[PDB]
Image (cartoon, rainbow, N blue to C red; front, side):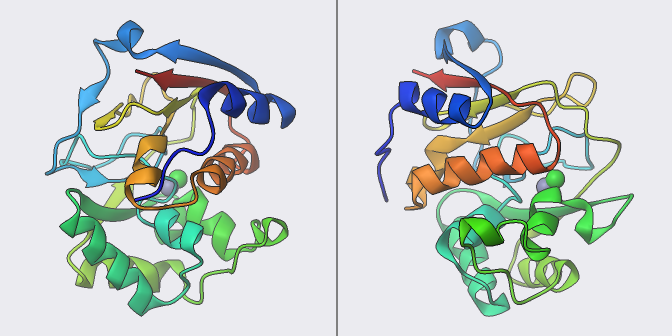
Length: 214
Ligand SMILES: [Cl-]
Ligand SMILES: [Zn+2]
């Protein structure tokens, strides 16, 4: 698809400029945690909470496949179904998620998007609600995952190691953003990463990041 027009040191610079604490960490220091992506795993949200997921090992993007629609300015249910099928055809099981406290509005990213919190960054709002979106993804062969508990993330990992990912730990949470996946889907990587950063910020998450590189 597209390529990383931005380097790791710059990502760190951009984040710090947004008021973040950021540093670069080598993949070799996480040999124990970095997992090769499993094609049977759902491409899911960066959310650090536990859930009822049984399809582990998939890439992590804000709102699951919503990160792709959001980055591309795709705002219709038909377009979302197209993306769902596209993701399935590209090696991952597509998904979106809700939670127990707010049901389908349980994904903070989609709620931020639907409510216009990305208005100032110039993003077109979706033209469907969280219930409509979830059911469209399901009807197109995707998965609706359900999270539980409170957001207790302590750090954000921005993984740039292609084909690998990190998994949720509900008792020692972290946001995980597979930046390499944005390139795989031809997304504007810089916008994707800035949106992921804004998401953590607006969800009142920790503005501390570790950028993982080969
Ligand atoms: Cl979420
Ligand atoms: Zn979410």
